[PDB]
Amino acid sequence: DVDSS
Amino acid sequence: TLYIEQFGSNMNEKVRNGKLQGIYGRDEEIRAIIESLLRYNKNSPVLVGNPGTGKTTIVEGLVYRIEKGDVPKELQGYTVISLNFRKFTSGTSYRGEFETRMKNIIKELKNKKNKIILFVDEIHLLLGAGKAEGGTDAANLLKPVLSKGEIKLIGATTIAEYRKFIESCSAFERRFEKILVEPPSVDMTVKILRSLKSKYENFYGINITDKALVAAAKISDRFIKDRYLPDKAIDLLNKACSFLQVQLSGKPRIIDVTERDIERLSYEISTLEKDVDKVSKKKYNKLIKEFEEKKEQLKKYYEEYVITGERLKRKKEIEKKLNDLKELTQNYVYSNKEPPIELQNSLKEAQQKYLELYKETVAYVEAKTHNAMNVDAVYQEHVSYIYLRDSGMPLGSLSFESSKGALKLYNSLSKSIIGNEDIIKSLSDAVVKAATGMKDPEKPIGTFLFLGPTGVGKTELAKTLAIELFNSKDNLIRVNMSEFTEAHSVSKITGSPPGYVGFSDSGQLTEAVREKPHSVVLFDELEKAHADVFKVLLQILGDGYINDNHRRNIDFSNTIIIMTSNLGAELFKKKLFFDADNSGTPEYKRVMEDVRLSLIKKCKKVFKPEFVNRIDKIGVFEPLNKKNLHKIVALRFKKLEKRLEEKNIQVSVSEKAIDYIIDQSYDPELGARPTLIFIESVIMTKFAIMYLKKELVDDMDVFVDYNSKAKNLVINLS
Amino acid sequence: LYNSLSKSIIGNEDIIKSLSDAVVKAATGMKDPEKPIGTFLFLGPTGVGKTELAKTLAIELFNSKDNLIRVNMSEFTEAHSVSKITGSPPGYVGFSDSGQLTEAVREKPHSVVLFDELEKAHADVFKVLLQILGDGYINDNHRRNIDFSNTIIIMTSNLGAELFKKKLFFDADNSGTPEYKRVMEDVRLSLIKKCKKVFKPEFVNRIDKIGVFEPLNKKNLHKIVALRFKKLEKRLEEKNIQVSVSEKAIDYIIDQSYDPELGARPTLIFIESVIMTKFAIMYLKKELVDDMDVFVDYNSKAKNLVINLS
Amino acid sequence: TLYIEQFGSNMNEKVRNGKLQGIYGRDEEIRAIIESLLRYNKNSPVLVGNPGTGKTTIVEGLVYRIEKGDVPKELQGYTVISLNFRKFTSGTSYRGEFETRMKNIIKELKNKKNKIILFVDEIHLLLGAGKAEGGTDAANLLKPVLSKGEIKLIGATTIAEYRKFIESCSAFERRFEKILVEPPSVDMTVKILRSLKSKYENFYGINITDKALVAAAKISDRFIKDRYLPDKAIDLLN
Ligand SMILES: Nc1ncnc2c1ncn2[C@@H]1O[C@H](COP(=O)(O)OP(=O)(O)OP(O)(O)=S)[C@@H](O)[C@H]1O
Ligand SMILES: Nc1ncnc2c1ncn2[C@@H]1O[C@H](COP(=O)(O)OP(=O)(O)OP(O)(O)=S)[C@@H](O)[C@H]1O
Ligand SMILES: Nc1ncnc2c1ncn2[C@@H]1O[C@H](COP(=O)(O)OP(=O)(O)OP(O)(O)=S)[C@@H](O)[C@H]1O
Ligand SMILES: Nc1ncnc2c1ncn2[C@@H]1O[C@H](COP(=O)(O)OP(=O)(O)OP(O)(O)=S)[C@@H](O)[C@H]1O
């Protein structure tokens, strides 16, 4: 789960 | 005056001027020359011996006994001349000139009124001299007249020069008598160094403790094999006295290194700051913190230079006044009184004040190990410093911080190596034998055997050890023992015997040990190796004295011998060890010790029983539990940051995300490898494919965390 | 020599009675003119003192450890390792020196020649060895004659140790009676019959005395441990730390780590890995003055303790 | 003005000319030579080590410290001479010329009023020089002197040349002192390459990013095993 946060 | 006197040099005049004053007694060797000089027939001894054993010092000592009269009177009054070839061969230009040079030399030596006994430095050079196209050799001219007794001659050659050059012309041999110069037998060499102390104390001005004199003998002789004894034992004091002059006439070494480095790190601040702000921000901010803290270390360093400077002068003040008033006040002891009041008032403080200043130095030497500031005394730590430098231990590990890092080894090993704590104590204690100096000589330190199933980290203990004990990957002299399946591959160890290809190089394993005598030697898999290779190593475990193609002794002292080998793949039970290891029981303690006793019995069958007793500690590594493997995976992510320093991508992981990596690929039958295959072939791909497509900027931190709901890993990017 | 060797090693007095008697021929000069003084062939289990008989002869007959010529036979397992002894024949690399062994014997013509691990060699090195034991007449590369007269030749090999009648005489012989001693003659004869089949029976013709070492008894090994502590100050003489040990603590070292099959190398490691390491880690932290009187004593409470005095 | 300057090239004139300008010296290495250059007997260190690991760099770094003055006050003003084996073979016209050639060299070395110190490029050589049919072994001409401290001398060879030739004599070897040069342990080589930017920037007009420098080292480290390290990182940058 790629999350840019 | 005489015709030979301008050739070479007159050795007798230099004794009169004091250039060659004094020799230690080698009286059985010296009187053997005097008797050979008094013989009826030949009167030409040759000092055959090893190159370092002082063959010329016998003759340099023999001239001192002539002029001072310690000879029988039949040899009284002769003068001794050396003959260098720098002056001897200058007249060989014209065709009939060198024989006239030889003719007048014989005409003076045959004279009895001309009392000269001749000396040459190395006779094997003299054979090939004066060989013109119409002219004979200088040795062949001497052969009819050296048999005649009137020409007195003394010479010295080394053994390897005497067997190659004199023995090629056997007729030239019989004119000469051997007198064997012998190696000086270490317990006599201690008396040689004590004889030479006042000569060094005048040239160097530095006090030399007798602790260093024994350390200049036993450490020099027993630990280094070439350059026979007095060329070793005198050499370290020749370096000990030279080492302290630079720290006294100049600054001490620590201040000298730090002042050069801060000037260099300030130059690197000029390189990074002018560049554009980027990835180099992290290294620039690293170097600014390094620049200040090393500069603040100076402020306590100069304090130590002044305080030990005050300690040195205050000891030097009492050596000028009361030390001389103790000794010179020896006059009128007989009746004008030697022990009344005030004669002892100052003698009383000479034991109180001087020994207190002495103990402040000795406590400072053990604290600041090899680089004590403002110390006029040579110590064992100074002699070991020179030994450790020329033997080749790298400059920032384990000996320059003497007796301080050996305690911190077991704490440092655990981070690098979590599991299997019992074997690591034995690796720590073996270095404790090394760092203290207390060990068996001619026995290699720490001949460990590492048994176990695959992937429990048997070679890890060894890869991390060279990084830990030496801070250098190159000191891990790994040899692939799995290469030695053939019986005839034994010659890769010791090399090829003479008369075969590759004799000029030595053995491929042994040539590295001459380069690196302080090294942790590997043997990767003794499980898969032929039994004839075991015959050769058998030597290296009981003694350090394995021999080469040239039979040069090799120092496997100060060499930790780690031997990983398997002896498994059956016999380590599939259901009583692999699957049951998670449940922490004392039932471990009758199953691990049970299976170990068969493994030592297995070494009696596959290896030899001579390995069973010579190996110091047969460690058997436990198969990996969850709690240890939870931190072994955590290590990989610490190692993953090192692969990503060039790209500035820090990687971090939550402990729940570690557990899902464990639960998908936990096989104790392998252990620690399929977890890394699950890391490097699955998790590492999106560390990789998210860079090709632009999901990873070069400054992005990653925090892997298990969702524990949606069941898939999440990648936290900032 | 017979009293000096018994103080230095606690070995079989039978081998020493033969070894010291061969040396008597050297001083009298009545000996074999072209045969070496006292050829031997030592045998026994691993770990017992087959080499240190030949090592203390450098210490007693010559008082010089370098005068021993320790030829490590284990590097001669390849068949073409003959050329280290006699050297390379002319026309090849390494013809300048006479050889790795023969240059050493010419340098010191009075030496105890040591062949550790005679078994671990190819049969070709055995062929040259028949010349050395029968005559001095080995020849060099340049055909220089050598004299192995005035040189004791001592070879040791590990053969036996499976034939040597295992645990019956290892584990059960804790005391030497005539009842146990009758086994050793029956094993020694089978060792000689084993020596015929591997070591090419004509070797037995040259060898003057085939000694066989017995495995170490607890009363036998008790004296050896006392010798190690006398040698323990020899590495501490530069540090001046005297280390005396009471006899009951020596009994605790033996009873915890006695392995009669291994020749009590585990007793020696148990010294170096336990009581020496505690001497070593106590020197790191500041508990040891360079002058400390040290007296190891066992307090009979399942604990050894190290008594220290300044 | 020296006779030896005709045959050995003078290292000391290069630092005054600016042929070498600032050396990243190895601080614990260079001072061992200075401690060997003052000695009661030997006075002859040799830099045993590796083909690409900076042997000259230490002695070029030594002259940079002598000419400016960082050495102790005894060694100040000493002249260092790099010998040229192309100029030793110019003699030997028929016979005896090389002994005139040798004796004039050693006489200036005996004078302490002369500040001269030899630097042999490779003592791998000197064994074949001057050996004619009547030859008398140029290296063995040095043997009666080197035991005394009359000749200050520095050497620098590889380990393979040290084993194949220097140990063959076994009496020529004992006067020299092995000063083991070590490969510079990557973290220092980044500090090397950052000290080499200012010369490389001006010689090319090309800026070098510091991210390429750690990339120039780390690709050179593991990925090429032979040709020891300072040859690799300097060339792959260059
Ligand atoms: N008994 C001794 N007394 C004083 N100095 C000694 C003694 N033995 C050795 N030396 C010193 O150690 C060196 C021994 O010199 P030598 O072995 O004769 O070497 P050499 O003079 O070059 O002749 P070579 O090289 O052996 S052929 C000299 O520097 C001596 O000062
Ligand atoms: N105790 C441990 N500490 C740190 N890393 C470990 C440990 N055990 C295993 N590893 C890791 O798992 C791998 C172990 O490699 P090794 O097992 O030493 O190679 P190897 O020793 O030849 O394996 P075997 O047992 O001979 S098949 C490496 O990736 C290590 O980083
Ligand atoms: N009879 C004995 N007298 C004195 N010391 C002994 C005796 N037997 C064994 N030792 C000691 O135990 C060790 C014996 O070393 P050695 O066995 O001679 O070496 P080695 O002979 O090559 O061994 P093997 O049998 O060939 S594996 C040394 O530490 C000796 O001091
Ligand atoms: N620490 C350093 N400081 C400055 N320059 C260096 C350093 N290390 C290496 N170099 C450079 O890299 C080159 C390496 O030189 P060396 O390794 O000494 O080769 P060499 O001078 O030809 O002697 P050889 O071939 O190794 S016997 C030199 O020309 C230096 O300019």
Image: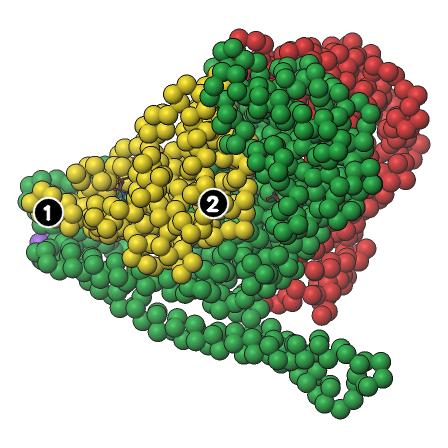
Chain colours: A purple, B green, C red, D yellow
Circles 2 and 1: CB distance less than 8 Å? no
Say which residue label 1 marks: D202
- Whether labels 2 and 1 belong to a single chain: the reply is yes
Amino acid of disc 1: Asn
Mark 2 or 1 closer to N-term? Answer: 2
Quarter of the figure with the C terminus of chain B: bottom left
User: Which disc is residue B668 wearing?
Assistant: none
Residue D64 in the image: x percent, y percent? 29, 52
Q: Chain of mark 2?
A: D
- Position above or below: B254 against C135: below
Say which residue label 2 marks: D110
Mark 1 CB near ligand 4 (8 Å cut) = no
Instruction: Name which residue lies at 52% across and 76% down.
Output: B313
Q: Nearer the viewer, mark 2 or mark 1?
A: 2
Q: Is residue B150 rendered to the left or right of residue B496?
A: right
Q: Is residue B93 rendered to the left or right of residue C187?
A: left
The Cα–Cα distance between marks 2 and 1, rounded to whole angstroms, is: 44 Å
Instruction: Name which residue lies at 93% across and 26% down.
Output: C28
Quarter of the figure with the N terminus of chain B: top right
Instruction: Name which residue lies at 39% across and 71% down.
Output: B301
Q: Chain of mark 1?
A: D
Are there few (<14), some (14-19), or many (20+) residues within 10 Å of tag 1? Answer: few
Are there few (<14), some (14-19), or many (20+) residues within 10 Å of tag 2? Answer: some
Residue B623 in the image: x percent, y percent? 45, 42
